[PDB]
Amino acid sequence: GSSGSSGKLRQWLIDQIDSGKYPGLVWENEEKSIFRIPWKHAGKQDYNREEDAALFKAWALFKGKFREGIDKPDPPTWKTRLRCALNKSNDFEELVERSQLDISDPYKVYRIVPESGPSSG
């Protein structure tokens, strides 16, 4: 809020969804507990990367320090970094059950598991 003293994904990410700045990223519910992330794969080079890494870029720049313009950017690092954290986060649940990657617009659903929440069930 005031200053990014302690960086983190749990909140950071949530902030991105609530803000609704990036497309696809929307809260399936009002409680802002469950959301959906757009999972696509172009591969092309001429295609626009900025957008593809619109959210990923922020993640890194936020957590670490990426030199924009001087240091050569690498989507792999960003995607891998986040993609990995998403799963690494034990406070996150896999809603793949509802996830739809076989439709017009593919996306992966996830549930933010709290601390005082029932691990099992």
Image (cartoon, grey):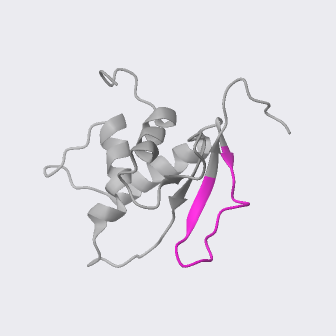
Nearer-the-camera pick, 5 or 113: 113
User: Which residue is found at the position 48% from the left and 40% from the top?
Assistant: 14
The residue lying furthest to the left in this view is 70
Instruction: Tell me how many marks there are.
Output: 0
Left-right relation of 74 to 92: left
**Where does the image place residue 59, in percent across and percent down from the top left?**
38, 44
The residue lying furthest to the front in this view is 30
The range drawn in magenta is 93-109
Give the prevailing secondary structure in the magenta stretch. Answer: loop
**Where does the image place residue 34, in percent across and percent down from the top left?**
61, 47
Q: Quadrant of the C terminus?
A: top right
Residue 47's place in the image compared with 35, above or below, is below
Residue 101 highlighted magenta (yes or no): yes
Nearer-the-camera pick, 24 or 93: 24
User: Which residue is found at the position 40% from the left and 28% from the top?
Assistant: 7
User: Which residue is found at the position 60% from the left and 48% from the top?
Assistant: 29
User: Which residue is found at the position 38% from the left and 55% from the top?
Assistant: 22
**Where does the image place residue 58, in percent across and percent down from the top left?**
32, 46
Residue 104 highlighted magenta (yes or no): yes
Residue 82's place in the image compared with 54, above or below, is above
Q: Quadrant of the N terminus?
A: top left
Left-right relation of 62 to 71: right
Left-right relation of 104 to 116: left
Residue 37's place in the image compared with 65, above or below, is below
Left-right relation of 120 to 31: right
Nearer-the-camera pick, 15 or 70: 15
